[PDB]
Amino acid sequence: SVITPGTNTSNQVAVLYQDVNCTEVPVAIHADQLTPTWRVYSTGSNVFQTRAGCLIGAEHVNNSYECDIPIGAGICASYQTSQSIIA
Amino acid sequence: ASVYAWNRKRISNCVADYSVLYNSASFSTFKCYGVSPTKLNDLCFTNVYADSFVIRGDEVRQIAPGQTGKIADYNYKLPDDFTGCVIAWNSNNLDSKVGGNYNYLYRLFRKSNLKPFERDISTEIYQAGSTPCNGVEGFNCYFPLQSYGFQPTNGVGYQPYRVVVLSFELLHAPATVCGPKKSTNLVKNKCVNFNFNGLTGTGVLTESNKKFLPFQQFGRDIADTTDAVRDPQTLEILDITPCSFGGV
Amino acid sequence: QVQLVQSGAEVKKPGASVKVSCKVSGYTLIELSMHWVRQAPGKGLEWMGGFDPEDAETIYAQKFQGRVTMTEDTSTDTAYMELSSLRSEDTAVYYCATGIAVIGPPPSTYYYYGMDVWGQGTTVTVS
Amino acid sequence: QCVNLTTRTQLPPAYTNSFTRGVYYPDKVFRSSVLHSTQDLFLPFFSNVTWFHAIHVSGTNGTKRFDNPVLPFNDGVYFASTEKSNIIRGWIFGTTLDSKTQSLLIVNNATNVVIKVCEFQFCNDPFLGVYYHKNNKSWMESEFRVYSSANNCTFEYVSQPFLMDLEGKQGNFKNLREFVFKNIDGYFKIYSKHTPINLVRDLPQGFSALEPLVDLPIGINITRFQTLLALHRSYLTPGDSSSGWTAGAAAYYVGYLQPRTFLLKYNENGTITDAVDCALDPLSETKCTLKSFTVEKGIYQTSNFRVQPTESIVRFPNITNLCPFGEVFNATRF
Amino acid sequence: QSALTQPASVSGSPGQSITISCTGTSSDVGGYNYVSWYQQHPGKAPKLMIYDVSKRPSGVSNRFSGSKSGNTASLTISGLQAEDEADYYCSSYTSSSTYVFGTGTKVTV
Ligand SMILES: *[C@@H]1O[C@H](CO)[C@@H](O[C@@H]2O[C@H](CO)[C@@H](O[C@@H]3O[C@H](CO)[C@@H](O)[C@H](O)[C@@H]3O)[C@H](O)[C@H]2NC(C)=O)[C@H](O)[C@H]1NC(C)=O
Ligand SMILES: *[C@@H]1O[C@H](CO)[C@@H](O[C@@H]2O[C@H](CO)[C@@H](O)[C@H](O)[C@H]2NC(C)=O)[C@H](O)[C@H]1NC(C)=O
Ligand SMILES: *[C@@H]1O[C@H](CO)[C@@H](O[C@@H]2O[C@H](CO)[C@@H](O)[C@H](O)[C@H]2NC(C)=O)[C@H](O)[C@H]1NC(C)=O
Ligand SMILES: *[C@@H]1O[C@H](CO)[C@@H](O)[C@H](O)[C@H]1NC(C)=O
Ligand SMILES: *[C@@H]1O[C@H](CO)[C@@H](O)[C@H](O)[C@H]1NC(C)=O
Ligand SMILES: *[C@@H]1O[C@H](CO)[C@@H](O)[C@H](O)[C@H]1NC(C)=O
Ligand SMILES: *[C@@H]1O[C@H](CO)[C@@H](O)[C@H](O)[C@H]1NC(C)=O
Ligand SMILES: *[C@@H]1O[C@H](CO)[C@@H](O)[C@H](O)[C@H]1NC(C)=O
Ligand SMILES: *[C@@H]1O[C@H](CO)[C@@H](O)[C@H](O)[C@H]1NC(C)=O
Ligand SMILES: *[C@@H]1O[C@H](CO)[C@@H](O)[C@H](O)[C@H]1NC(C)=O
Ligand SMILES: *[C@@H]1O[C@H](CO)[C@@H](O)[C@H](O)[C@H]1NC(C)=O
Ligand SMILES: *[C@@H]1O[C@H](CO)[C@@H](O)[C@H](O)[C@H]1NC(C)=O
């Protein structure tokens, strides 16, 4: 599942892989066969574990905000400040 | 030409009337794939290629999409999505000589099956054994080409059949060759059953300012309807509009 | 690189004709303009025999015309010469010279006025 | 002929980026404002394209190194060369590239382009021998340097040259000569767009489509690739002493198409103006799923285009004996 | 058909400058600037040292130079050594499409 802002606003995206463990993210999508543009989303510093799945590309923020993009399982995404996707 | 080097000839800038052939000879096979023969008269063709060769009668069935055999695997492979026709006729009076005619050849052995419409003219010694052939024929080393050897007293399957297969492409390009349907006067801005360049349909014609590249003959709008077409006689680009607007 | 090979010496008799060859290697004669030379001891060189790159011809000085002719075989890359009516005056050594057709890159058609590459020559002598 | 023009040593090739280049028209039907998706052999975006300094100058003593090695054709070849001097003037397509099997040869001379399909006994170092013949005062072009002998010729195509006559630079500019070669179902397809480039170093972040040019019915197997260079004699200067065919410099680029799914966009005039590679990035996959370039804010489920089969494996039982079909079919009595 | 004037009696000390002169008619030397000199050792093939008056080919040292102004042409030898004592010629293209030579010059160290 791709979580994105408007294309006019930005081109940055985040990806949720549904109902899989984060350590099994490279195994599930087989990032060895994939392009490096997919492999940078396969494993990175911005990795979060949710009940819905493993979310890569959004930085976890302890501060709670109102939901505008429903990720699921109680986690929500927003494009905030220079500009990044926060979960 | 023989089947291992099948002669391919482009045909262009003409009208293809099948009637002329009627008197000369009758064809044993006229299977057309992708087109119907009864509508073969009323179509323009963008580019036609005739592939001419001679095979045996029992191999006549092998000239077809999705078939295998001697000729289909090692000599001449037709594509799966083949928009063309196959013509075959017996030639015992022509291609058979008393005592045997050995001009025509076929490829009995090959390493792999042929990809569609691929010609192999190689005569290299096929390796049928573990040891290398080293360019010398012997046991487990065979020449790839073998002769037919037609005889006048041979059986029907063994008689020579001349096969020409015509490959078409329709309604995607300007048509250099077309069928023998008499052209009539063009009437615009009215509902009419028009046949323009192989496009048959009932509709209303409209003059519109649409520019076509020279390689683009037929124009399709959004949701794949044919909005525009280039008339062959007059190079104006003509918009196609429905007979009834249907908003009643 | 560009090596010119000669036919060696040919001693003759007065009144006869002398046949000489010049073989190229590493480069073809169709791309090479060739000049001939009549080197003799005690006297400077004189220009008898050349293929003008500018003129698609092979002309010689006024003193030596008709007495000598030029035939060229481009198949074997061998350059030939017929002399005629030599009566005890041919005491000289014949160098085969050549130069570039047109110097510069392929668009350039600029002419070359040179006799750059030489051979070992042929020491003909008439007694 | 067939002399050694290359040295005994070579250098590793340079690698640079294909900044979203190499899209071509996959259909001849005019389409206006249609975001039509099409699956075909396309060059992947942001992929390694192999820079080949065929002739590289370095200082003074190291004059030039010559290298034009044979390459596997693979699925297809994206060829781009940005040399103003018109050094690159042909390609040879084939299998053995020998007289055992036939091969293709496109030679683009100034007067006409000649495409011949014969069994060509190519030289080890193929090139076009430009030279000057004193007889017609003509720098004439010799083809014998390409191949030793041609036999069993099956095709011949003569038409207009397609390199813009090697002119139109107007100073401080370069022309990017792009080409795409595809061999499908017995047909050879060549696509080509030539554009003025300002940066002489690498590919433009700019986008252009490759118009269909020719569709020759070659009918040959094509597993290997090489290009034809134009070289002049090294006896160019008076007193210079080199017989080698040394000339200019060539910096062509070779990229390999791979099967991919793309969403080409056709503009009002019928011109592709943008395209999206489905497997390139998660966002591009979202654009492929929604079939629109503008993606609204939110979460979207996307279908698979990212992964492709790398190879193929077959597993059959351990079987040694051949079947007695010769026993059944060739029986004396049925 | 004519011949160019060369002073056949020249000599000098090593490491000293000698100018070798070639003078000819307007018909031959006068027509063009294409006069080229040589370096023929006795019983050896001649070498080309300068072409088109001054342009010298690759493989010759800086010691050899030449200039032609008006009609008379000159070859200048500097940094003389013991191997340069040889017989030298000047050769000029004429309007009659002929490359006439000179009598030749003998330099002795
Ligand atoms: C088109 O041409 C290519 C190249 O000639 C053909 O592929 C080649 O097929 C042969 C025979 O199967 C291969 O030879 C064998 O390869 C295996 C390893 O793969 C090796 O163990 C054997 O000793 C033998 O060398 C050859 O390698 C292979 N070459 C390539 C580059 O794939 C292909 O069959 C031809 N296709 C058609 C449709 O004609
Ligand atoms: C460029 O190639 C063309 C190919 O057409 C050459 O033209 C042919 O030259 C051959 C051999 O000289 C002739 O026998 C043909 O009659 C010519 N064909 C036609 C119709 O052009 C042309 O000579 C080449 N030009 C160069 C040297 O660049
Ligand atoms: C391809 O070329 C070869 C060699 O020229 C041809 O083989 C010869 O064909 C001629 C003419 O038929 C015969 O006279 C020779 O006896 C043949 N030699 C051999 C050893 O076969 C071959 O037929 C040509 N093939 C095609 C289809 O063009
Ligand atoms: C992008 O959004 C800004 C602010 O909403 C707006 O001013 C601008 O016109 C938009 N651009 C496009 C291309 O929609
Ligand atoms: C994920 O990891 C946990 C341990 O942290 C394990 O209990 C669970 O079974 C794993 N689930 C999967 C999808 O393998
Ligand atoms: C949230 O709190 C945890 C407490 O362990 C801390 O490690 C983490 O860095 C905090 N993250 C942010 C975004 O403040
Ligand atoms: C066909 O002929 C008519 C008149 O005979 C002419 O007006 C028209 O332009 C022609 N069209 C073509 C395609 O030659
Ligand atoms: C030319 O190259 C080939 C292949 O490397 C080699 O076998 C041959 O001996 C070389 N010839 C010369 C002149 O070195
Ligand atoms: C190109 O290949 C190199 C290997 O040297 C690799 O590091 C690089 O990531 C590749 N380029 C891309 C865009 O993947
Ligand atoms: C020179 O050109 C003419 C006319 O094109 C031609 O007939 C003649 O054969 C040419 N000569 C050579 C040597 O190519
Ligand atoms: C297409 O190109 C023409 C010029 O040939 C121009 O007049 C027209 O506005 C363009 N239309 C578009 C935007 O596609
Ligand atoms: C059938 O059997 C006969 C026995 O003489 C043999 O000659 C012939 O080649 C066989 N045909 C095949 C291989 O089916």
Image (tube, coloured by chain):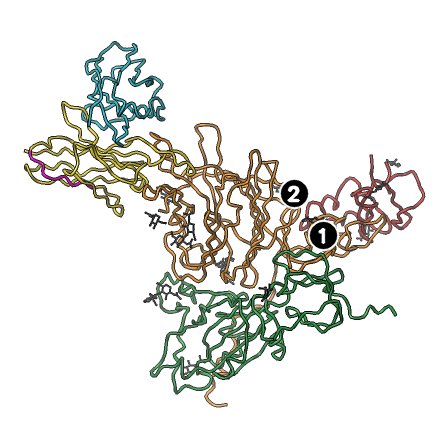
Within 8 Å of ligand 11, the CB of disc 1? Answer: yes
Please provide percent x and percent y for residue E58.
36, 26
User: On the image, numbered disc 1 is attached to which residue?
Assistant: D267
Q: Which chain is red?
A: A
Q: Which quadrant holds the C terminus of chain E?
A: top left
Please provide percent x and percent y for residue B59.
50, 78
User: On the image, numbered disc 2 is attached to which residue?
Assistant: D19
Q: Is residue B233 above or below residue C28?
A: below
Whether residue C95 is visible, yes or no, is no
Q: Between residues B207 and B226, which one lies in front from this camera angle? A: B207
Please state which amino acid type lies under the numbered disc 2.
Phe
Does residue D4 appear to the left or right of C63 in the view shown?
Answer: right
Task: Check the rendered structure and report the hue given to chain C.
Answer: yellow
Residue C86 located within the stretch drawn in magenta: yes
Q: Between residues B184 and A42, which one lies in front from this camera angle? A: B184
Q: Residue at the location (57% across, 51% down)?
A: D180
Does residue B198 appear to the left or right of D72 in the view shown?
Answer: right
Q: Which chain is green?
A: B
Please state which amino acid type lies under the numbered disc 1.
Asn
Mark 2 surroundings within 10 Å by alpha-carbon count, few (fewer than 14), some (14 through 19), many (20 or more): some
Q: Is residue D297 above or below residue B242?
A: above
Give the Cα distance between marks 1 and 2: 21 Å
Q: Which chain is orange?
A: D
Whether residue E13 is visible, yes or no, is yes
Does residue D106 appear to the left or right of C98 in the view shown?
Answer: right
Q: Which residues are magenta?
A: C80-87
Q: Which chain is cyan?
A: E
Q: Quadrant of residue B125?
A: bottom left
